[PDB]
Image (cartoon, rainbow over all chains, first blue to last red; front, top):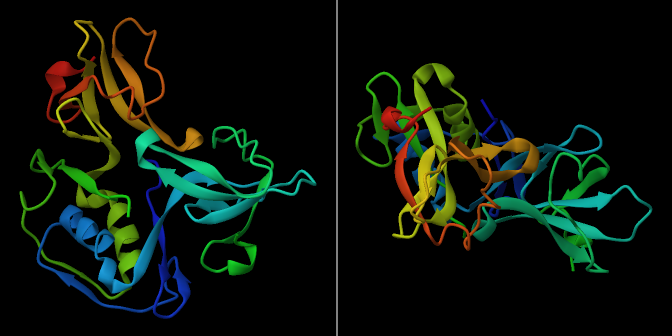
Length: 127
Length: 127
């Protein structure tokens, strides 16, 4: 009942795919679960997969892995959404600059954040 | 580079699928990302999808959503692995009985846990 879904950055065409941005035809002779796994783990197809976190920002925008958010604070910081296996969580990684926050990523702490770009479509936000 | 993968409980055949337990043929006229999303969200196919957490138990067994673990403690408790959207995390939900733990789900806290069953293949562990 939780939404499980992904967006993809196509490294060949420099394009983010959510639904039908791109066309295709997939064919596999395996079950649904094995199919998802095969696709997710085909690195040479040139798609980078990013998972929807299950949280929405200040504006109802769905927050994905690889998103860059700001705390609608008047503050100078930028954060990157990362999944960290070792804490089995999505969390914020500081991109800029004062490295002091950012608490747990949760429904409370994102109530005043905004998605501003992501690490693929917005290199101007990087480093 | 983090492993993203799923297992599925087939509600029609009462069987857990990881790789080739089940056969099939999938066909879609869309891109990889849209394909994964379609499959994940087809409830009427009768697969319940469960995500790999990114953590392994005391024995190197990979921990999934829906797993039932014990703390290799001599303790009486059982926990269920759940994903909670609102904290964008996998966490333990107490199944039995003394409701007092269980800290964050992380590489430290599972170093002494063991996967014992899951909420589908092990109804004897439930409630």
